[PDB]
Amino acid sequence: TARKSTGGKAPRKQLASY
Amino acid sequence: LGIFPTVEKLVEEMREQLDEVDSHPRTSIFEKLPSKRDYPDYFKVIEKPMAIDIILKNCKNGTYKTLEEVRQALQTMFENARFYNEEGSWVYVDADKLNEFTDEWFKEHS
View (tube, rainbow over the protein chains, first blue to last red):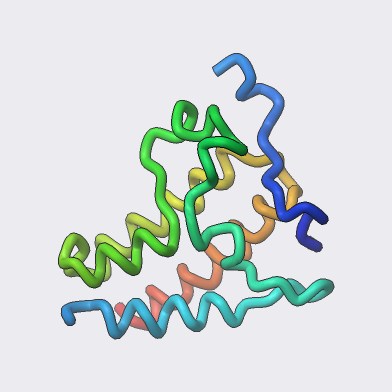
């Protein structure tokens, strides 16, 4: 899959409560 | 130099695995750990951080002396990517594609 334009990661939403 | 020459060649082969659309090396995101500034929770969420630069350094400094250690470090690195990132995201896909490549590499070298 093409790299995200910023080069940034894709952190899962559920980790906000980890 | 221990296993460092063998690992340097493996990493070069990994870096030659490019995305079919934009040609980015699938190793790109794995070369170094995320910045704590950009991802403040990364080091809270990921218990055993790992990246390619760390793997190479550990083969140079004698921390990893066996391919088994390198295989476990790569497995952890890819598991960290799959745990942290959304399924189907570019990082997740690169982790899966590279992990399939390294699985075959280890088979051929075992």
